[PDB]
Amino acid sequence: TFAKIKFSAQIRLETGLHIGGSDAFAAIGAINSPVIKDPITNLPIIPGSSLKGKMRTLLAKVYNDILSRLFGNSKDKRFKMGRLIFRDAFLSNADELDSLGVRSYTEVKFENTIDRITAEANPRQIERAIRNSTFDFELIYEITDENENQVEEDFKVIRDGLKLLELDYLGGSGSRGYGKVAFENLKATTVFGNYDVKTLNELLT
Amino acid sequence: TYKLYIMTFQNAHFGSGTLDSSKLTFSADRIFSALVLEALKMGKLDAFLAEANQDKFTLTDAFPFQFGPFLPKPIGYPLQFLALENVDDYLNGELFENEEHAVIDTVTKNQPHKDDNLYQVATTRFSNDTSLYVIANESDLLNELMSSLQYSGLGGKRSSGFGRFELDIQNIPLELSDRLTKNHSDKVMSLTTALPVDADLEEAMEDGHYLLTKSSGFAFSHATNENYRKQDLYKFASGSTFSKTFEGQIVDVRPLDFPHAVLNYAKPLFFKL
Amino acid sequence: KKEKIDLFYGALLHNIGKVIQRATGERKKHALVGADWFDEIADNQVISDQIRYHMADHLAYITYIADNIASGYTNQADIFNVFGAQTDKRYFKPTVLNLKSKPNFASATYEPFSKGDYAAIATRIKNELAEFEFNQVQIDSLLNLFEATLSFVPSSTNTKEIADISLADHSRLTAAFALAIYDYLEDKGRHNYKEDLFTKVSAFYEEEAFLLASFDLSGIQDFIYAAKQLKARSLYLDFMSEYIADSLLDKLGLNRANMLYVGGGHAYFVLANTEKTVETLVQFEKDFNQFLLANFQTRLYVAFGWGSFAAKDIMSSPESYRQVYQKASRMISKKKISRYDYQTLMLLNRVCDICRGLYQFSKEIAHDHFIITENEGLPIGPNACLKGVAFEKLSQEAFSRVYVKNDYKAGTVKATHVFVGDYQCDEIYNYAALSKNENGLGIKRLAVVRLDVDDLGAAFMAGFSQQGNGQYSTLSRSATFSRSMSLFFKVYINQFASDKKLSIIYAGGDDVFAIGSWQDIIAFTVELRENFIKWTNGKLTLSAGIGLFADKTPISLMAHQTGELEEAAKGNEKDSISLFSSDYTFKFDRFITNVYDDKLEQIRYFFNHQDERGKNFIYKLIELLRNHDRMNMARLAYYLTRLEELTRETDRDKFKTFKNLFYSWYTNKNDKDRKEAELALLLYIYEIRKD
C-alpha cells in the first residue's frame, strides 16, 4: 500500500520576494542583499527549506502529533523524518517574462532607514525577484502502513498550510511587503505505487 | 555486472563528516542504506536482505556521467575521475583536467526564533548533464526500490530539497563490461568502498595502493527515540588498486545494545587494468 | 661517546681560524690560527689537535674527509643570486642576527669591505665560548651561537664558483658529514685506520654511505581547521615537527645539525647508511605512527623515506642529485599511499582528553620557554609531554624550546631555538571596533590576509636549475635557501607587524594567515611584499588575498573566503593581489606603484583640499566606473565639465586638474587605470566614512 502522491503547484509571486543569501563582500553602490540563486543558471530560486520552515511555523500557530508527522522530529521514534519531502522551486515562466518585456528576472529596490532624531537617512539596496515570477513547486507526501488511517487528515493540513502561506509572506523581508504569493493549480498525482488521486483533487481547488 | 543506474540530481548534499561540506559523490554505504530504508518503508526489507547477503548482488560507488561513464583514478600507477575511454590512456601516461561536474557551494540557513541556530549547508549543484550511475545486479525488486528512491531523495538534508533525482537504467558499454570481475588475479582496482575479510587483509595491505575513509555517523532508526552514533569504521576507498580481487563483507556497525542491525555495504566490485 | 663528542666539536670548530684570519689578519694558515686560538679556550687536547690537522690522531681524518665532502677579503654573496636570472651581484654585510631588529637586505654595493667589524664578532665568540664544558649537554647551544654570529660571514671566499654558503653552514654541514662518517665506520667496525681509506685513496667516495632520510607530517593543513586557539593548534603541529626531528636524532647517535630544511611538515636529514639506522628508522616510524593513531587517528601521519647517496654524488652529477631526492620522495609517497601495518588496522576496527590539553596550551601560548616533560600535558611523542613555561621553572626538563630570540633566550642549557609565532597585539574581537582613527572616521572592518609564496615546491628543488645546465644546486645551497625562507617568514614578519594592530595566526611561507584591522592589514601586506622583494631581488614572488569582513563573524567562513580570494589571485599570473573580491585581482606591482602611490594619493590630495565636492561626487564616479558603457564616457565627460563651472573660480583650476586626471584614466582603453581607479575610490571612500 506504499504510494507517493506528489503535489505540484505554481508559486506566483504577487509581490516580489527576497529569500536571503550568503553574506559576501558587497561594494559601495552594489547590492546590500542579493537573492539566493542557482549557481549554474543565475536565476532566482525558492529553497525547499524556506517553504518547509515557513509552512511549518504557520501550521504550528494553528495546530497547537499532527505537526511532527509531516515535518519530522529527531525525538519521538515513530515520526523521525516524517512523510514530506520538499524541493527547490525554479522559475517556470522564464520565457513568459521574456515575452512581456522584462530585462532582468530580479529587481533592485532602494530603501532607507531614517533614524529618529537626528533624522539622518541610511540607504539600502535589496534585490527582489519580480512579481509575476512563477516557480515550479513540488511536495512529495508518502503513503505507508501507518498512514492509511490518517491520510485524509494530512491533506487538510497541507492544503490549510498553503492557504495560510497565501495570506502570509514567504521567505524574507516581509511584514513590509515582499512575500505575497499565490498557489496556482493544486493537483496531486501518484508518481510511485497505487493510490486514487481523484478523491483529494476534489477536496483541492 | 548488469545495467547502469544513471541518477540526475540537481542540488544534492553528500556530507563528508560535517554539514558544511559536501563531497560530490556517495559511496556504496549511502546507496545501500538508502535501499534498505526504502525497503523498510515498503513491506520488503527481508527480501532485499536475502538478495543482498547473496553473492551475486553488486553495488558500486557513484561516479560522474556527463556523456559517458567516469571511473575513479587508479591510485599510484602514473586527478579524481577519468573518462571510461581515457582509463587505459591515463594508465600509460597522459594528463587530464578534473572536469567541473558540479559547483559545491554553501548556503547560510537559520532557525529564526532560536537566535543561536545559524548554520550552513554545502550543496553539490550538478551541471545540467552530470549523473552518477551505481552499477548493480538488475532485479525487479531493485528497480522498484530505486524508482522509489528517486521520489524520496538521496543523501543529506532531504525533505529540504537536497538529493531528489530521476532514473535512467542503461546498458553497460561493452568495453567496460569486459573489465568488471570479482575473481581476477592480476592488477585490479576497487571501484567501491570495500573492506576485506581478515583472510585477505594481509594480501590487500601488502601489495595494495589505497586510501582510508572513515565511515562514521549516526544510525537512522524508527525505533530508538534518541540517536546513537555508529561504530566508526575505516575502509578502503574507491580507486584503490590491489594485487588481486578480495572478498568483502557487509559490516554490522550497530550501536552497543541496539535493536536492529546497522549494516554497511563493503562488498567490492572490481575493474581490470 | 667520548670519541663522537670530541669529533663533533672539532667538526664545528673546523674553521674558526677563518674568522680569526680576518680579524687581526696574518698570512699564516687559518688552521694554525684557530687551533692556537682554541688552546686559550679550555684547552681540550683532542679537539685542538683535530683543528691542528683538519686541513692536512685518528679522529682528524674524519674531519679531513668531512671538509672535502662538505665543500664539493670578498663579502658573502646572497643565495638568490643563483636563481633564474644571471644579472645581479647583491652581496651581504656581516654583522649579526639580532632577531629583534631590522633585517640586513643584501645590497649591490657591499662587495668591497669584508674586513670591518669581525673583531667584535670574534670577541662575541671569545666571550660566550671560552668558559665551556664541552659535554654533550652543551652540544646544543654552540649551534645556536654559530647561527647567531657566524651566519653572515662567508666561507672560503676565494673567487671560485661557490662564494655563497656561510661559515655557520659549512661548519654545520661538515659536522653532519663527520658524524655520519663516524657512524658508518664504527658500525661497519673497521677503523684501522681512519686514515687508511680517507687521505691515501679517494675510492671511499664511490660507495653508498649517507642515507638522506626525510619525513612528511601529512594532514597538517586539515588538522588546523576562538582563533588564538587556532594559532595554538598550528604551533602545536610546529613543535611536533620539531620533536620528531629531535627524538629521531636522539634515538640515533646524533643531534641537530644532522638536519636541513625543517618547518611546515617536511624535514631532511643526513644519516649513516648502516643497518642500525634503517631498522631504528622503521622502528621509530612505527612507534610514532601508532602514537598518532592513539591521539589523532589518521588525521596526522609521519612517513619516513630515505635515499642512500654516495659521497661523490654531491662532489661533481646534476641529475643524480635530483635522482637522490627522487628516491627519497618516492619512498615517502609510497608510504603515504600505503599507510599502516596489518594488525594496526585489524585492532583499529573494533569532555575531551587532548582538547583540554590544547585549551591549556592556548593559555600557555604567551610564554617563550617550552619544556619537554614526562607527564605534564600536550603529548607530542611517545613518552613525551609539552608545556609552556616562563622563567619560574627548573621542574624536570628534557629539552627547552626557546622562542625566536635564540641569543638572549639562550642562557639556559639544552636550548633548541624555534622560529615561529608572535605579535598578537589585541584580541580579535576588537580589531574591527578599532580603526577608529584619531580623527574619528573609518569603516569598522576586520580584514584578513592569506599570502603565500608562488611556485615554492618548484623552488625548493628546482630554483637553482636555471643558471647553468651544470646547475649549482648544492645540498648546502638548498639548506641556506630553506633557512632564508624560514628566517624571513617566521621571524622577520614579527618586525613587519611591529605596531600594526594585527595578529599573525600562522606563517610558514607555504601560507601566511594574518587577521587584523584593515588599513594596517593592507599596509602589512604592502610592506611584506616590498620587503620580500628587497629580500629576494625578485625571481621569487608572493600572492595574496585580502578579505574584508564585519565584526563578530567566524574564522572558518572568513578563512575560506579569503582562501578563495587568494586562489583567484593565484589564477591571475601568480604574482597578484585580490583585494576584497573575486575581481579586483591586480598585479602586485601595479597595486603598489599605481594604486597606493599614484592614484589614491592623487584622490586624497584632491578631496581634502576642497570643501565643495564631497561623498556624493565620489559615489557618482564609482557608479560610472562600475558601469562603463561607451555612453558613460560621454556622460562622465558631461558630468565633469558641468561641475567645472560650478566651482568657486579659486578651486576651478584644481578641479580642472582632477577632471583631466579622472577623465584620462577613465577613457584609457587598456582597462588597467579604470578598475585601479575604481578600487582607489573604494578604499578612499572606505577610509573617510564616519559612524
Image (cartoon, rainbow, N blue to C red):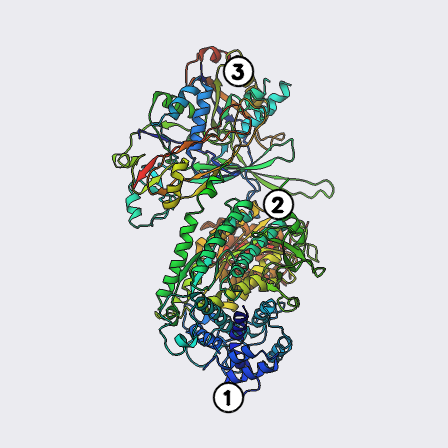
Q: Residues within 10 Å of mark 3 (few under 14, many from 20)?
A: some
Looking at this view, is C590 or C30 the one in front? C30
What is the CA distance from the residue labelled 3 to the residue labelled 1?
105 Å
Amino acid under disc 3: Phe
| SS under mark 1 | loop
Amino acid under disc 2: Cys
| Whole-percent x, y for residue A91 in the image | 46, 30
In which quadrant will I find the N terminus of chain B? top left
In which quadrant will I find the C terminus of chain B? top left
* Chain that bears disc 1: C
From the viewer's perspective, is the residue at label 2 or at label 1 nearer? 1
Which label is found at residue C28? 1
Which label is found at residue B209? none
| Whole-percent x, y for residue A133 in the image | 48, 29
- Give the residue pinned by disc 3: A155
Residue C267 visible? The answer is: yes
| Whole-percent x, y for residue C363 in the image | 67, 51
- Give the residue pinned by disc 2: C355
| Whole-percent x, y for residue C673 in the image | 49, 58
Looking at this view, is C61 or B122 the one in front? C61
Residue B90 vs A90, above or below: the answer is below
Does the residue at mark 3 contact the one at mark 1 (Cβ under 8 Å)?
no
Q: Residues within 10 Å of mark 1 (few under 14, many from 20)?
A: few
* Chain that bears disc 3: A
Residue A94 visible? The answer is: no
What is the CA distance from the residue labelled 2 to the residue labelled 3?
50 Å
